Image (tube, rainbow over all chains, first blue to last red; front, side, top):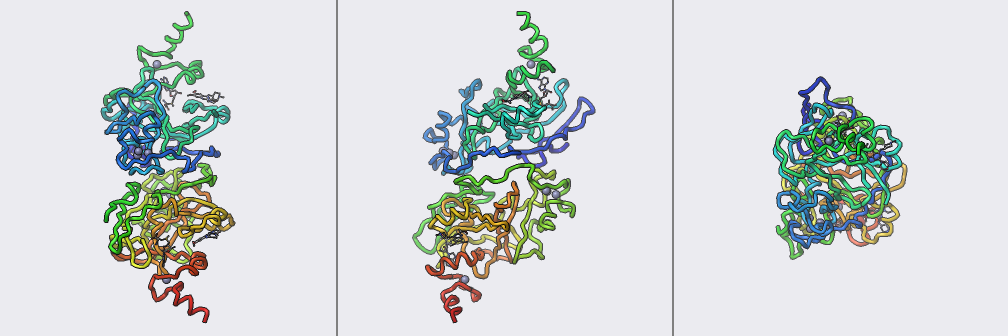
Length: 263
Length: 267
Ligand SMILES: COc1cc2nc(N3CCOCC3)nc(NC3CCN(C)CC3)c2cc1OC
Ligand SMILES: COc1cc2nc(N3CCOCC3)nc(NC3CCN(C)CC3)c2cc1OC
Ligand SMILES: C[S@@+](CC[C@H](N)C(=O)[O-])C[C@H]1O[C@@H](n2cnc3c(N)ncnc32)[C@H](O)[C@@H]1O
Ligand SMILES: C[S@@+](CC[C@H](N)C(=O)[O-])C[C@H]1O[C@@H](n2cnc3c(N)ncnc32)[C@H](O)[C@@H]1O
Ligand SMILES: [Zn+2]
Ligand SMILES: [Zn+2]
Ligand SMILES: [Zn+2]
Ligand SMILES: [Zn+2]
Ligand SMILES: [Zn+2]
Ligand SMILES: [Zn+2]
Ligand SMILES: [Zn+2]
Ligand SMILES: [Zn+2]
């Protein structure tokens, strides 16, 4: 498959399988931006946007939008700072339409979409996954977790929860089971190389942050991308199946889980 | 020619401003936006399942495309220009392909959602203040730009005193809404009225199909020469209100809103 994204992303995203006869997945709708099925009532009031007054490229410390994360966390190249808290990331507020800066300012990384070459491919033990077709320096924006915005009440009534991302006031979830992007195919890794960060762009409704994946380290060509699904995932799912990341750091293998109960 | 792009890089192309008539600097008492904004909720139907979509897997140039069928037929040609036969007097509502469609994004039913492609220039006119012109020829049927502004209700439009930048959206059912580009708008806010206009508005649906909120796309109604001023017909509601304050200066011999013209009708 030449482009699973049907031209909706900045770059084509191919699918390959060199492991078995399983065909490229088609039981979902590809979308490049979050969708709704019943109103979420996102606050789109342009006068509720906090914005900056910059006349430069927003690389100075006086930029309010940068100040909303204590400081802008991007360097000149669009990458997270070396000092960035990869354990507890702050909320990033990117420049918006209420700002006076141009569209090519330095605070517009995530909203400018995918730039690295990625591949949907068949793994050996985890079904489909995504890997890099190129080296990727630490701090690089990879892709966004795109799906269907739903409420916790609705998340409760859905049988399939294998593609849920939590957004925790009142709680909401991103559900990429029926509608989603390339992110829906990223596997859980006990030794992860991408992290999620909560980000705001066109609106600043704090109930609905958007999820951006950045690299936590240098990633070699062909390396599988993975993040930490967290314990709420594994507390539910482990009585059905156990982790196959194979790391010696694995925290969710049948082996690891059994060693724990002995103690 | 001080400002190289009034859109601050938000459009596919830059839109420069020049003034060769007086000392008035490039206008800045408004905010440039490349898309419609809200100030109080419009509650647009954004239900992705309420989208009518097609099953096309080709470039949607087929007769089978449901999206094209919604306007009876896709009215764009292979180059993205309106058909010669397009009703330029009472234009149909056009439904372009969307995210629920199975076609790729480089489909042939996606002209307006692909944004501006011709070179335009904000410039100082002689008798009408600021205007917009072509820095290139524009063939008939070509998409120029969209009328972008603040989505408000008819009720709210009644309450705002400055009404020089309003476009009416009169849905069949009633429940009328307006685009107000006085405080927020794009290059379209600077386009002047022409009694013999060379652009027409078309109502278009793209990312949503909330019928209360058509998006307004301007196409050329005829060939336009390089340097020609762009204009549409603002309509009678505009002039029925404004002509007791000022009169039309389009200078056409077809003008129907000049002091001359207005005086001739009383008999
Ligand atoms: C990050 O991964 C998961 C997040 C999940 N989040 C919720 N909710 C958020 C809180 O508010 C109730 C919803 N429910 C799940 N599961 C429910 C459990 C109950 N089931 C009937 C419906 C799905 C999840 C499951 C996840 O992985 C398996
Ligand atoms: C296309 O041009 C115009 C459209 C206008 N539309 C409305 N509406 C509110 C009432 O429903 C219909 C849409 N009001 C205007 N103006 C005034 C606003 C001030 N108010 C005291 C009376 C109505 C307009 C003015 C226009 O140009 C001068
Ligand atoms: C969001 S999906 C990722 C795409 C999925 N691998 C596929 O083939 O469609 C998450 C599901 O993939 C499988 N999976 C993901 N990470 C795994 C892991 N670390 N170990 C074992 N299975 C995993 C499980 O079926 C899990 O419910
Ligand atoms: C939406 S604006 C167009 C931009 C405006 N000329 C400017 O410089 O800001 C509408 C206003 O432009 C002027 N105008 C537009 N067309 C005109 C015309 N044909 N004759 C006289 N004045 C016109 C009127 O003042 C009208 O209220
Ligand atoms: Zn700034
Ligand atoms: Zn900025
Ligand atoms: Zn800003
Ligand atoms: Zn593991
Ligand atoms: Zn089609
Ligand atoms: Zn379509
Ligand atoms: Zn199409
Ligand atoms: Zn006239």
